[PDB]
Length: 47
Length: 51
Image 1 (cartoon, rainbow over the protein chains, first blue to last red):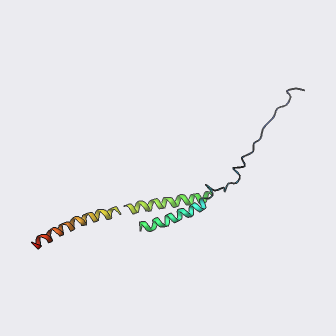
Image 2 (cartoon, rainbow over the protein chains, first blue to last red; image 1 turned 90 degrees about the horizontal axis):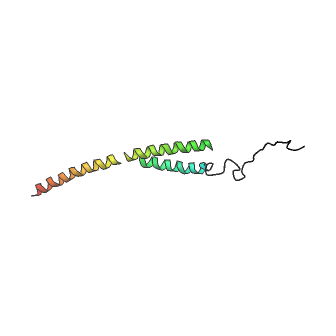
Image 3 (cartoon, chains in turn yellow, blue; image 1 turned 60 degrees about the vertical axis):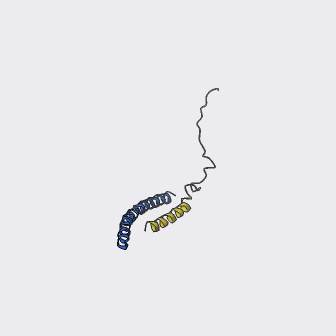
């Protein structure tokens, strides 16, 4: 035969992407602790 | 992760609210300026009484 075959295609993500808890967005934990510290200090200052 | 970010948003909102509340210190400066003008008057009356 000839020109008797078509083809589909699939896709893989990036390795650098890896997980979802990869800091800069997941380290919002540590940052939240910073923000809570900020909030406590501001509460005192406003008082 | 989403929950922590939401908590961070709420925290920064409250911090901003309180900071604005703190700023509304200016009423204290206004009052201190008023009391300063009064004390300037007290000083003038005292000087006159010395004479």
